[PDB]
Image: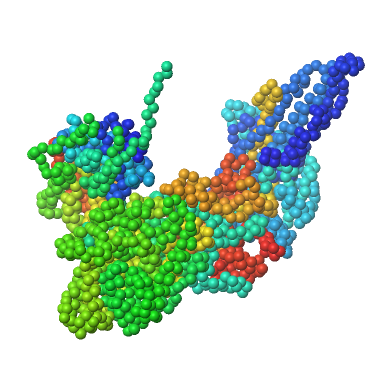
């Protein structure tokens, strides 16, 4: 509860309003936020119907020990031109400095702005204090459905409500403007797979080897490798994720790899960088890919597929057995501005 | 405390009594002169008085040439040694061969070139000359006071100058004896290396093992040999063959063999010097009388000086040479002169034949053939209060177990001991005899300063050392890992999706450990079970993250009973539960005759199905049972008369209501007695559980919630019919989550949206049509709202429900129990749509089956053989009104206890349990009416004690197809449960609990076995078992260290070392106004002229034992200070219940606890090997092969080199990542000798490099000397430690005894005592020192 009053002094003047937010364990258990004191939070908001990017601000978070209980934060709210937008996502990115951890937690302003609604010279000494009392108002997250609390601290103030500027006609429907990200990334994945299937047709519905791996001679194994490709087309199309490898490659300034979990046997680990490997496509460059410990297991093993994305937005789908199909993400110049603004 | 520790303690306390004796400043001084002012000069003028004092001289010592130590070294006086940089000796060893007529290759000529060097030594002493004393040395004297002032200053300067020359002749003999002792390896190493009958094949891998196995055997059998021969019959004949063994093991291969340095008076030569202390020398004169007491050696040093030809090459080239005149008279004067022996002996004798002879007084002796001088140089180290170097302090390690369990065919040998022959008694302590023969106990409450510490209780330090051992694990089947939640309430849907076309059945790592015996798990054909036996308290598995390769995680075991059968066997849990009985003094109300009734109902093939229909209609309700008590008094009576068994045994609420609400003669009096005895037992169990839990509280939370799991209310009973889920939330610090399908349930303020209550039926006669409207309209596959009755806190108690379903029913049914689910609207469609129920023309008090038609009720009532009246079924029809919907399951995720909130991953802090709402567990359904059960009921396997295939195959014919297709899964321990109902790793009851109940005997002692099996395995439960002297689920081994003041015997052969004595050079370094100091330097070089070893040391006599051999555990709160629990009120509670002016026995020995499975062998603890469980000898394997020496320590593909049968004694301490490897591999830790990987790999080299390093370099971190708490040593100035366990990697066993009486039998007869009694043992000590043991008057040597 000290973490609210610290941010009013140092995050405060760099913002317009702060959304003082306390996250209970029920919200923490869903997103798997392991409360160590080393975690460095960072916040930025993704605008709608405007050029969407704001500056990243580092926000202090402290665990509250016990009347709720959970992680305490403070989210920045940005009023460009004197008013708030209702459909405007405030993104929280959770990461550790040393170890490998990256989480994205997103909040919408209508779940925040609504919840805010109810002689020697003397030197001034203003310490940080928890003297101000909290008012705890309920909220539910739109994206996961897990409850979190919002603090409203006591201080043309009581006369007005907090401003909003609702969107105007013509408009997409608000279930499709809320998930503006998950409907843009999904149609870049559904058009990526249509390039992978197009390479089968120009070859004659075949899968050719690329990686020298000896395959045991059994007829049931040769029919099982084909089943890993068709399962990989069910997973790449359903995948609409903020942290995919091709978003990391488009916002890069290095091969970006993401392994999949076929038949839901594994959760996905996305955006792994292949440092020291230049995916030129020559046969001497696949030895540097095989020196990675993941591709030795996505190929010798089973039930895991693997996608390796070049910085030129060309990607191979690596199957077990060394079979691969070159595919291409098509990103126009208008969409690179849309991606490098909101994500990079 | 500064008077004693300062040296010369008798002269210090006497000279510090001057402050009491002194009264005037001229007290002790004499009067000599008078200084008048004239000739009489007045009676009133100032007269002066010259005072004289008494000074005592510095006690001088015998010079270096007149000591008999110089028979071991060759003395030359090199005048300018501070100009020398180096000095070398170059050997050229030509080697002959044998020419033979076999087929192998003849050898060509071979040579060796050996290069020795010179070690240089530097000595400094300081001399203070007072400035008032120097000033009058140059002044003019003309009066008789200035002559006696001058003569008192010329004596002060010379006495400080005789002092500096004294401190260099002490400095010679110290630095020669320090050179001799660094190249003096002991007897037990060198006796086998000195004999070339062992190394004639070359030191192979199998010769080194036979040679290290003689390092151990001579260290035990022949050590302290002058103390072992005080109590032998032979005596002199044993010492003489021991001391002519030291005499011949030394190689007499010296360049100066022909040079005759010292002789006897008769003409023979003195072969060596045998140097002891004073106490050993006066016993070697009585065994061996002196023969001459006279020798004749040189009187002066040989003089080497750089004269006119070496001095040109010393200046200009910077290299000089010994005796240029011989090198020039051979290279140019006789260039073809071959090296002959006698023509060269004048040149090799470097002036040591020219030195004038003299008469040296030294006590010789004759040993077989050789004349050997014997000294004792203690009289020069006592005069200056420095420690003598021959009083080395040998430091041995010791180990003994405590709390083990001996296997099932228990035997004995003894005929004396009577009182402790019971099979139910188990020792929880071992008795160790102290240094002063005070037999002390090492219990668990003495063992608690290091157990209850969070280095013993986290896997985050242990899953990282396991991840550097096997960095790329194959995450295979991810079976029991996590609960995949899906939005269903149709538990017939999630059941039928999972067993439809299942052809492959997976077994986790945990369910295949609880079936393995205690000896199959340690056999080296099983890596994989033994690999993840890392920690005692936790339970490891492989998680599929990150990427495509796995990683290791851990879940806590939470109980004593989740320890597997190899590490806590079936007869141990019984004999731990019979100790629960003896302390609380509970009395079993249940006899064996009533378990004989409950067990016969559980295995009944003709159990009536109709008492499931009643129990589904009551569903645990107060009001609805009273309406039906004239019906259930017929179902019980017609099942007790028709057969000897009794009905309504399934759930707790039916057994509770029969005992309380009748109080009459409705049930027969014999049959009603068996029900009263059930609730007589359950109340008596929770009377006992509230005694051991104690009265005290940590904070807001009592300790009764935190010692056992049968009292912790976060463990819910498996069948809940009331609003138990909100009564948990309002009284919990451990924050719970109820998962009703998809939506979590967090707060009690959101109760109405998730939980819908239904009160009395008499109160709900108004809103009762609104119930039936929701039976038809609502979608019950996605309703996400559970229906339960409101609960009254003065009516129930959760412990009696928890003592019923988790203790008494898995025993008495032997685990034949499945969770039967009910479809309720299909039950009453049989009852109400009868026809004799509906038609009011039929008489109410008439028999049913006279009027009833061919339906299911004709077949269900033919099973129970019941003839009820029409009033009876019509009351059962009325229970349809407030009857709940389909049986649901709610997963209660709560956080773990504050002693258990250390986890590898983030989900690992949360323990979980699925509670079947509105369902009831049920036995094997009768096979004559499976057709009627197939129209009403369906099975829900949701818990380890409630997932049984032989019961679940009866309820639905698809699982009867699943059991008969693959008969692997016919066991309860093995059987697969759907991933939407249970994950085993996120669970309280975690299969080794479910494997005990299937193999019981259903004994009244097996009831109390289960109650002492739900004992929390945490830190503040170990306090509550240590007060009552219980046994927690693990034994432990102790490790100590003990010092010995050993008086040694050094032998050193003739003329081996050759010394180079420089000249003393005075350097002034300070001038003050008060005094002038100086510093006399004196540089010595020394070289070893022989090739092999030329001096041999041996422990001869123990002067004293320094460290007392008493129990004192090392508290881990001082060593790891930064660790703490999550609480502060619970870290201050444990630190309070766990934990010097002056000590009485001696320096306290630190004891270190290595926890161990309770099935480990006692026969390991008798033979002296290390407490790792595997041997750590690295001298055996190949030289400089670091990859090969690691397979000895940590690989388990091979058996350990000690035992060809097993692989490891304790897997909790041997392996990579285990708790022994986590704590002690990185105050003083005796376990750092054995576990530290870097220190063990120093002994991988060739065994002659180890012998050179042995005596020279001190080992890795030994203990300090004469400090109260046994600290770790640093700077090693006067530190004389000799630890032979750091090389051999073994610890020697002590006296241990599980009971007091076993040690009273060892005293009375040393031969015929039984080493293994029934439950108790005794380790007879196998140590390199033997002692007298006196307990009273009786002596055992």
Q: Nearer the viewer, residue B1324 or B262?
A: B1324
| Residue A87 x %, y % | 17, 40
From the top left corner, tell me how far across and down residue B637 is, in percent.
33, 81
Kindly indicate the quadrant of the structure image that contains residue B542. Answer: bottom left
Up-down relation of residue A115 to residue B1074 (above or below) = below
The residue located at (57%, 61%) in the rendering is B430
Quick check: B1287 above or below B575? above
On screen, B395 above or below B1307? above
Residue B1091 visible to the viewer: no
Query: Depth check: A339 or A57 in front?
Result: A57
Q: Identify the residue shown where x is 40% and y is 76%.
A: B674
Q: Quadrant of residue B538?
A: bottom left
Quadrant for the N terminus of chain B in the image: top right
Residue drawn at (31%, 56%) of the image: B726
Residue B75: x and y, percent? 70, 39
Q: Is residue B912 visible?
A: yes
Q: Nearer the viewer, residue A236 or B1253?
A: A236
Which quarter of the figure is the C terminus of chain B placed in?
Answer: bottom right
Image side of residue B1086 versus residue B467, left or right: right
Position of residue B1196 measured from the top left corner of the image (x, y, whole percent): 43, 59
């Amino acid at each position: 509860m000290d973490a609210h009053a610290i941010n009013e002094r140092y995050v405060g003047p760099r913002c317009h309003r702060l959304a003082h937010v306390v996250l209970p364990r029920t919200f923490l258990l869903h997103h798997a936020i392991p409360l160590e004191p080393e975690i460095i939070f960072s916040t930025y908001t993704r605008f709608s119907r405007s050029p969407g990017s704001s500056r990243r601000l580092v926000v202090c978070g402290k665990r509250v020990l016990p009347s709720p209980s959970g992680l305490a934060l403070s989210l920045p709210l940005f009023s460009h031109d004197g008013n708030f937008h209702p459909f405007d996502i405030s993104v929280l990115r959770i990461s550790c400095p040393g170890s490998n951890l990256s989480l994205t937690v997103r909040f919408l302003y209508l779940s925040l702005v609504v919840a805010m609604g109810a002689p020697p010279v003397r030197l001034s000494f203003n310490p940080v204090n928890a003297d101000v009392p909290a008012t705890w108002r309920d909220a539910t997250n739109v994206y996961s459905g897990a409850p979190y609390y919002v603090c409203v601290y006591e201080r043309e103030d009581d006369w007005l409500p907090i401003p909003l500027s609702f969107p105007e006609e013509p408009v997409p429907p608000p279930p499709s403007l809320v998930f503006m990200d998950d409907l843009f990334i999904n149609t870049k994945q559904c058009d990526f797979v249509d390039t992978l299937e197009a390479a089968c047709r120009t070859q004659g519905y075949t899968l050719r080897q690329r990686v020298p791996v000896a395959i045991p001679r059994d007829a049931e194994i040769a029919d099982a490798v084909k089943s890993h490709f068709l399962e990989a087309c069910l997973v790449l199309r359903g995948l609409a994720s903020e942290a995919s490898a091709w978003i990391r490659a488009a916002t890069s300034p290095a091969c970006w790899m993401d392994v999949l979990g076929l038949w839901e046997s594994r959760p996905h680990t996305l955006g792994l960088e292949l440092r020291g490997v230049n995916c030129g496509g020559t046969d001497g460059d696949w030895l540097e890919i095989l020196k990675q410990p993941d591709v030795q297991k996505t190929v010798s093993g089973s039930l895991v597929a693997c996608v390796i994305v070049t910085p030129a937005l060309e990607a191979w789908l690596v199957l077990p057995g060394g079979f691969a199909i070159k595919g291409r993400y098509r990103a126009s110049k208008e969409d690179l501005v849309f991606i490098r603004g909101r994500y990079g | 405390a500064t008077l004693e520790q300062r040296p010369f303690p008798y002269l210090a306390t006497e000279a510090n009594l001057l402050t009491q004796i002194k009264e005037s400043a001229a007290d002790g001084l004499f009067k000599s002169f008078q200084l008048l002012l004239g000739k009489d000069a007045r009676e009133g003028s100032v007269r002066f008085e010259a005072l004289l004092g008494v000074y005592t001289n510095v006690v001088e010592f015998v010079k270096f040439l007149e000591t008999a130590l110089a028979a071991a070294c060759v003395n030359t006086e090199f005048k300018d040694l501070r100009r020398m940089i180096d000095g070398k000796i170059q050997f050229k060893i030509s080697m002959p061969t044998i020419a033979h007529g076999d087929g192998r290759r003849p050898n060509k000529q071979r040579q060796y070139i050996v290069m020795k060097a010179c070690n240089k030594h530097h000595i400094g002493a300081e001399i203070e000359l007072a400035a008032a004393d120097i000033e009058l040395l140059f002044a003019e004297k003309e009066t008789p006071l200035d002559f006696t002032e001058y003569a008192g200053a010329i004596k002060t300067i010379t006495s400080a100058l005789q002092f500096g020359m004294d401190a260099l002749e002490r400095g010679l003999v110290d630095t020669v004896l320090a050179v001799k002792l660094r190249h003096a390896p002991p007897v037990f190493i060198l006796k086998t290396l000195g004999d070339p009958v062992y190394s004639e094949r070359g030191l192979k891998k199998a010769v080194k093992s036979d040679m290290v196995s003689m390092f151990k055997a001579h260290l035990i059998e022949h050590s302290f040999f002058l103390d072992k021969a005080e109590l032998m019959t032979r005596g002199k004949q044993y010492v003489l063959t021991m001391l002519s063994d030291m005499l011949a093991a030394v190689c007499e291969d010296t360049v100066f063999k022909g040079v005759s340095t010292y002789t006897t008076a008769s003409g023979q030569q003195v072969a060596g010097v045998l140097e002891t202390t004073d106490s050993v020398m006066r016993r070697l004169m009585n065994l061996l009388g002196q023969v001459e007491s006279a020798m004749s050696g040189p009187a002066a040093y040989a003089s080497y000086v750089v004269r006119g030809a070496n001095l040109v090459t010393a200046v200009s080239y910077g290299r000089a040479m010994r005796n240029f005149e011989q090198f020039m008279a051979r290279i140019v004067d006789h260039p073809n002169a071959l090296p002959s022996v006698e023509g060269d002996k004048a040149a090799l004798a470097d002036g040591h034949d020219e030195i004038q002879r003299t008469r040296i007084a030294a006590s010789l002796v004759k040993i077989g053939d050789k004349f050997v001088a014997i000294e004792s140089l203690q009289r020069m180290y006592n005069e200056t209060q420095f420690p003598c170097p021959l009083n080395r302090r040998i430091q041995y390690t010791y180990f003994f177990p405590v709390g083990l369990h001996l296997p099932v065919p228990r035997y004995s040998t003894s005929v004396s001991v009577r009182g402790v022959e019971s099979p139910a008694i188990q020792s929880t302590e071992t008795w160790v005899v102290n240094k002063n023969n005070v037999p002390l106990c090492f219990g668990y409450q003495n063992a608690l300063k290091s157990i209850c510490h969070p280095r013993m209780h986290n896997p985050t330090q242990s899953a990282q050392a396991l991840n550097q051992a096997f960095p790329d694990p194959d995450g295979g089947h991810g079976y029991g890992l996590r609960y995949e939640q899906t939005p269903n309430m149709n538990l017939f849907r999630t059941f039928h999706q999972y067993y439809m076309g299942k052809n492959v059945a997976f077994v986790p790592d945990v369910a295949q450990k609880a079936l393995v015996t205690t000896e199959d798990l340690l056999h080296p054909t099983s890596h994989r079970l033994l690999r993840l036996e890392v920690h005692p308290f936790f339970d490891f598995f492989v998680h599929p993250c990150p990427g495509a390769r796995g990683s290791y995680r851990a879940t806590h075991r939470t109980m004593v009973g989740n320890i597997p059968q190899p590490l806590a066997p079936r007869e141990f849990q019984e004999s731990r539960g019979a100790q629960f009985d003896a302390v609380t003094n509970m009395t079993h109300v249940i006899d064996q005759l009533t378990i004989d009734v409950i067990q016969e109902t559980a295995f009944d093939p003709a159990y009536p199905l109709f008492c499931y229909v009643i129990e589904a209609m009551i569903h645990g309700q107060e009001e609805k049972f009273v309406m039906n008590m004239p019906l259930i008094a017929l179902v019980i009576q017609t099942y007790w008369v028709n057969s000897g068994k009794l009905a309504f045994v399934n759930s707790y609420h039916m057994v509770r209501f029969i005992c309380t609400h009748m109080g009459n003669g409705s049930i027969p009096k014999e049959a009603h007695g068996h029900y009263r005895k059930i609730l007589g037992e359950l109340i008596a169990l929770e009377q006992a559980l509230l005694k051991l839990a104690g009265h005290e509280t940590v904070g807001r939370t009592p300790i009764t919630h935190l010692v056992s799991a049968l009292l912790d209310p976060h463990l819910l009973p498996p069948f809940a019919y009331h609003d138990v889920f909100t009564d948990l939330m309002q009284k919990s610090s451990r924050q719970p989550i109820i998962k009703i399908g998809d939506q979590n349930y967090d707060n009690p303020q959101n109760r109405a949206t998730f939980i819908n209550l239904r009160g009395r039926m008499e109160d709900l006669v108004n809103n009762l049509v609104n119930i039936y409207q929701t039976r038809v309209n609502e979608d019950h596959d996605e309703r996400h709202v559970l229906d339960v009755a409101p609960l009254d806190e003065n009516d129930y108690n959760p412990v009696l429900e928890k003592l019923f379903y988790y203790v008494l029913m898995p025993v008495c049914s032997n685990g034949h129990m499945c969770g039967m689910g009910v479809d309720y609207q299909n039950v009453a469609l049989t009852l109400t749509y009868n026809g004799p129920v509906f038609a009011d023309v039929v008489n109410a008090q008439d028999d049913i089956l006279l009027h009833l038609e061919n339906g299911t009720l004709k077949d269900i009532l033919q099973a129970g053989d019941i003839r009820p009246t029409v009033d009876m079924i019509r009351v059962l029809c009325t229970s349809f009104l407030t009857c709940p919907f389909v049986t649901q399951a709610a997963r209660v995720i709560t956080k773990r206890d504050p002693a258990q909130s250390f986890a590898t991953h983030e989900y690992g802090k949360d323990v979980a349990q699925t509670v079947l709402v509105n369902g009831f567990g049920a036995f094997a359904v009768a096979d004559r009416s499976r057709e009627a059960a197939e129209t009403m009921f369906y099975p829900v396997p949701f818990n380890k004690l409630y997932a049984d295939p032989l019961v679940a195959a009866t309820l639905h014919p698809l699982l009867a197809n699943y059991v008969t297709r693959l008969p692997n899964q016919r066991n309860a321990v093995v059987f697969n449960v759907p991933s939407n109902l249970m994950a085993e790793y996120e669970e309280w009851h975690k299969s080794p609990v479910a494997a005990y109940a299937a193999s019981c005997q259903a004994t009244p002692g097996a009831i109390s076995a289960m109650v002492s099996m739900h004992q929390k395995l945490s830190a503040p439960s170990f306090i509550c078992q240590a007060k009552h002297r219980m046994h927690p689920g693990f034994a432990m081994t102790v490790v100590r260290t003990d010092e010995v003041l050993a008086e040694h015997i050094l032998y050193c052969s003739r003329a081996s070392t050759s010394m180079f004595v420089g000249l003393p050079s005075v350097v002034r370094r300070e001038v003050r106004s008060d005094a002038v100091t100086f510093e006399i330097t004196h540089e010595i070089a020394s070289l070893h002229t022989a090739l092999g070893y030329s001096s041999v040391i041996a422990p001869a006599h123990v002067a004293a034992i320094t460290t007392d051999m008493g129990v004192h555990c090392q508290d881990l709160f001082m060593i790891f200070p930064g660790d703490a629990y999550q609480d502060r009120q619970l870290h201050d509670y444990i630190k309070m219940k766990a934990g010097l002016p002056g000590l009485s026995h001696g320096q306290l020995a630190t004891c270190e606890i290595i926890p161990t499975p309770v099935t480990s062998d006692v026969a390991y603890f008798q033979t002296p090997s290390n407490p790792r469980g595997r041997a750590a000898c690295v001298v055996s394997c190949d030289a400089y092969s670091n990859e090969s020496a690691e397979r000895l320590l940590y690989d388990h593909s091979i058996p350990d080199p000690a035992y060809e049968c097993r692989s490891t004694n304790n897997p909790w301490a041997s392996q990579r990542g285990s708790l022994g490897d986590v704590l002690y591999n990185i105050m003083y830790s005796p376990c750092r000798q054995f576990f530290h990987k870097e220190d063990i790999m120093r002994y991988n080299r060739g065994l002659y490099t180890l012998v050179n390093e042995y005596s020279a370099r001190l080992a890795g971190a030994p203990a300090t000397s004469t400090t109260d708490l046994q600290y770790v040593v640093v700077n090693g100035t006067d530190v004389f430690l000799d630890q032979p366990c750091h090389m051999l990697q073994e610890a020697y066993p002590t006296l241990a005894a599980s009971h007091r009486v076993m040690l009273d039998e060892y005293m009375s007869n040393k031969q015929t005592h039984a080493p293994v009694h029934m439950g108790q043992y005794l380790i007879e000590e196998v140590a390199p020192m033997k002692r007298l043991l006196k307990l009273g008057n009786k002596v055992v040597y």
